[PDB]
Length: 260
Length: 260
Ligand SMILES: Nc1ncnc2c1ncn2[C@@H]1O[C@H](COP(=O)(O)OP(=O)(O)NP(=O)(O)O)[C@@H](O)[C@H]1O
Ligand SMILES: Nc1ncnc2c1ncn2[C@@H]1O[C@H](COP(=O)(O)OP(=O)(O)NP(=O)(O)O)[C@@H](O)[C@H]1O
Ligand SMILES: N[C@@H](Cc1cccc(Cl)c1)C(=O)O
Ligand SMILES: N[C@@H](Cc1cccc(Cl)c1)C(=O)O
Ligand SMILES: [Mg+2]
Ligand SMILES: [Mg+2]
Ligand SMILES: [Mg+2]
Ligand SMILES: [Mg+2]
Image (tube, rainbow over all chains, first blue to last red; front, side, top):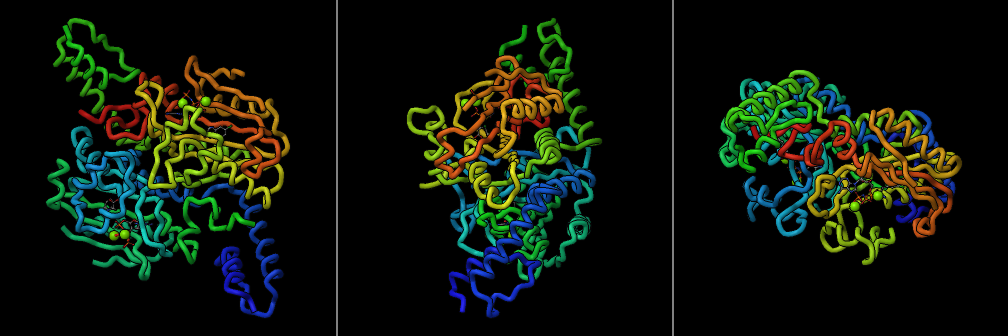
């Protein structure tokens, strides 16, 4: 019989599309050599043909979707002033206050895109015609307990529209077109707040403004927006058992173990 | 006559393609209203047509170049173990040792891509045919003195080939094809080491292995590689006077002031 340590080793080499019975009679060394051969072949095929990383490719595909729908592509700082966290209403009572990676005395790694998106909406309202539609994709950081659905370093899509047309119906239409474009099953469950679920996994939280917090950011128009984790989208699309398979990582490439 | 503070204000609104004499007789309020009008028009045109961010677009264009040349696209952690810095030979004597953004007790924001690229070359050598060609584009972080050519948060392209064909000629051919593809003037000046210059501005440092440091990373094959700053490429291509115009930023969008 396989030890638990041996099954752990085989599980890192197992891909969802495999159809191998680990619990059958075959010895560990033979099961391991078979899986090593397939994963090496998987990497050789990627190298010979497409050569694109799942996380980079997903970001490029989402970028094309939102640019084509009239949203301006934003690239804003990842290292942000610590004051932005408090100004978001994240005080000691909230969970997120304990999840911040602090840097130096006055900076942190952003755990969210909302502060920079607020700042862009306010500034662009002086220049662009109504409605203002923006989006950003990039790294975000949170301290988390170990869990199959959370990374400490992940990638967030955030989009926001401000001005006319900021209805819940329009928000649900964006989400619906977006996930049907990507081929990801979902249910929307519900200022108004709204979560996008895949089974028990949260793909997104979405919001409809105005809300009282807007005033602190110099915002006084209605808005709709949502934030999606890219690694969670990849986990669902590729049926990964653990989100570590979709992360920026030295241990996995497109969900394939790099320890061969 | 304009005050220095007024000229500073006008300089943030001035774009390289403008042809306005600030030192002429026109009053500040009129020069400011003219420049505000043009920059608002510039943003409106981006929003109406392409809607792509210069830094995102450049990353996508570089990605296509290297994928098409047979390099595997890597996305590796930005928050890296602090031990990687020492293992790179960065001790107290080097400048880079004082430039590290530390996070928690044992992590830092990566100032370079070399450690993760080394780790990928070693792991992929067990799976991929010779030669192994990889590249990564993403955020890097260094503490810097104020200067028109440096950001504390920037974006690095790093590529590396390991195995056969790792000659200086082949390295110079990659660099030359790459920058002629982008339309960026350069001179290459010179294990062997090699810098890619635009006038007095360093676009890249490049290297040819083996070097003694490889052994610490489990590497024992020849290699060639180089690292390029994306914001410096944008600064040259768009003739920005200060690299702040090309950065991830809340103050500039595609080199256009957002404070209008
Ligand atoms: N640690 C994380 N790892 C991966 N994705 C994350 C992480 N935290 C948040 N996300 C994603 O970012 C989206 C928006 O962030 P947010 O609504 O603040 O998350 P959240 O409410 O903390 N979700 P959860 O922690 O799963 O209950 C989420 O719906 C997830 O898709
Ligand atoms: N602070 C920075 N801001 C922007 N680009 C940078 C920065 N540091 C390095 N780069 C870019 O990354 C490339 C490779 O890094 P590296 O060779 O370590 O830089 P460097 O030797 O410290 N250059 P410099 O600081 O200008 O003398 C450089 O050639 C630049 O294009
Ligand atoms: N609240 C998360 C996700 C998000 C982003 C943007 C907009 C909304 Cl409504 C939600 C963040 O600030 O990044
Ligand atoms: N030395 C810089 C630039 C670089 C990257 C990769 C390879 C070479 Cl030769 C040079 C870094 O480690 O990121
Ligand atoms: Mg959470
Ligand atoms: Mg949520
Ligand atoms: Mg330097
Ligand atoms: Mg250098």
